[PDB]
Amino acid sequence: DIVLTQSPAIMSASLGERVTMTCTASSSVSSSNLHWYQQKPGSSPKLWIYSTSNLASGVPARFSGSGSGTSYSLTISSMEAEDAATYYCHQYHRSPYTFGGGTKLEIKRADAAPTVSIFPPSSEQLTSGGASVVCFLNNFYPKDINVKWKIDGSERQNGVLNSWTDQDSKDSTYSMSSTLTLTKDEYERHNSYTCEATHKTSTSPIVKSFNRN
Amino acid sequence: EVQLQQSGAELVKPGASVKLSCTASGFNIKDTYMHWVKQKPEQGLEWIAQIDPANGNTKYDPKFQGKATITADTSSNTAYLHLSSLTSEDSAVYYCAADPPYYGHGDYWGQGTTLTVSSAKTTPPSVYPLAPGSAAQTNSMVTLGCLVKGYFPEPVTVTWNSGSLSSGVHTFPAVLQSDLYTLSSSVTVPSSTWPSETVTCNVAHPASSTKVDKKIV
């Protein structure tokens, strides 16, 4: 098994910027058997560069690939919005045919703090004997963020479900939602519910809380 | 002219088996190598097996050996992938790919086929409105939300005011919680329009042919 390592796994770059990502094999392969694939969300992987340096049909000229042996690289002279995607290198040299972990290329932009919002359970939901507290952390950058739930100053990690959206197609920001699910009971036996989040954008953890009623 | 069409999305119960198909158009599969690739959700691509439709010779990746069986019917110009003793780890998208005789031109990959393994039954979503507990979340403007819990299978459609509200909307990807899906959609609107004008979130679950509307107070 020839292992392909791609680096970095995630990278950001502003438009017009030159971009280079690498792919190194654990053992040498024919430059002719190393290919790159582009994949955008929801779509199927597409052959981008074949045989190390040949552009596939319909691939922009700002793309180029280099290498031989165990080291390869894909370069974008001037990055455009439509370039944001995930790139996979693949070796069709010796089976089992392998794929690199891919490099996710995202659009870089000015840092932006998240606008938090905590939401208490629903009457309707409470009626069913369940209670879910939801916290929204919208439009921020970078994606790195750490949310914590505090029930009466106490940290709670049981029953939390987070979800992130992809880089916004318009403002290139990220969003996340975190839901803490408890019972009508164990929820009605606590007063303060806190949604805490630390973002590069701040050394002072952002907090949004509420008391029952 | 070259194109690979794959069979439709599949929903199967654990323990069962399924047989996916990949029909090639614009070219004979006898003159090439057919491949099946699997991609787990948010994971990477994994090559599974290859076959020479000319002699039936097959190559497998050890970890799939036993579980997967690749076959091909050159007469119908079709390649199949059979998966047995299904489990949730088999849930993923499956692509069939043709090793081109000429790389330069053509997209030799298939659209992919989604395979979901669940023992869950179609379940309509429980929609719960999310209103702000009275607190200045952000200067003036405000943010509302809707919680879509315990539904199956994916997907659901979350619109605000039937469509009149498609600005500042954030619908988060569904996430599995006890075999059912849960999702949430937030909506941002200038402090001047709420609670002034009424805001409703419309959820639709095709599989269950249900459409709910929830107003926020």
Image (cartoon, coloured by chain):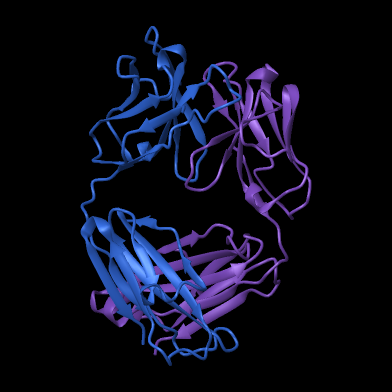
Chain colours: A purple, B blue
Locate residue A61: give its quadrant.
top right
* Percent coordinates x, y for residue A43 in the rendering: 49, 43
Depth check: B202 or A199 in front? B202
Depth check: A41 or B4 in front? B4
- Looking at the image, can residue B68 be seen? no
Q: Image check: B70 left or right of B121?
A: right
Locate residue B159: give its quadrant.
bottom left
The C terminus of chain B sits in image quarter = bottom left
* Percent coordinates x, y for residue B149 in the rendering: 32, 65
Locate residue A37: give its quadrant.
top right
**Residue appearing at x 54%, y 84% in the figure:** B137
A53 in relation to A146, above or below? above
**Residue appearing at x 63%, y 62% in the figure:** A172
* Percent coordinates x, y for residue A79 in the rendering: 73, 49
**Residue appearing at x 53%, y 28% in the figure:** B106
**Figure disc tally:** 0
**Residue appearing at x 31%, y 78% in the figure:** B214
Q: Residue pushed farthest front?
A: B1
A144 in relation to B145, above or below? above
A101 in relation to A154, above or below? above
A3 in relation to A172, above or below? above
- Looking at the image, can residue A79 be seen? yes
Depth check: B8 or A184 in front? B8
* Percent coordinates x, y for residue A121 in the rendering: 36, 78
Q: Image check: B109 left or right of A79?
A: left
